[PDB]
Length: 17
Length: 48
Picture 1 (cartoon, rainbow over the protein chains, first blue to last red):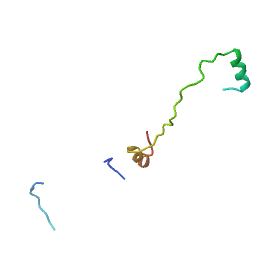
Picture 2 (cartoon, chains in turn yellow, purple; picture 1 turned 120 degrees about the vertical axis):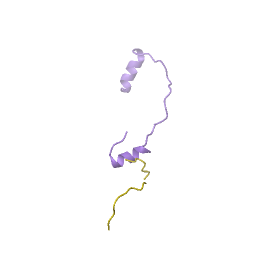
Picture 3 (spheres, rainbow over the protein chains, first blue to last red; picture 1 turned 180 degrees about the vertical axis):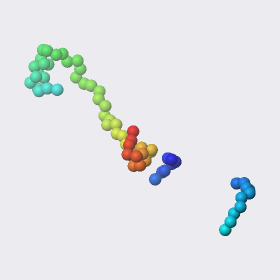
Picture 4 (cartoon, one colour; picture 1 turned 135 degrees about the horizontal axis):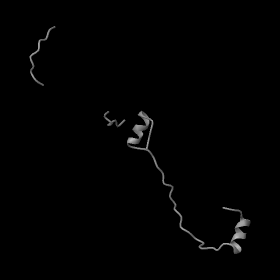
């Protein structure tokens, strides 16, 4: 992968603590 | 490629000389690995 080596949305969902 | 004796025996009357001077290259033609060749010979172990 790479081969370069030189060297949002408001969605209703409950959240608890 | 031969010995001087056989060379003389061939050049006297067997073979015939065509030319005495010729053109010859003067370059060796080096080669080195760079670019993407160095990076693929360290993480994989191959090169082309």
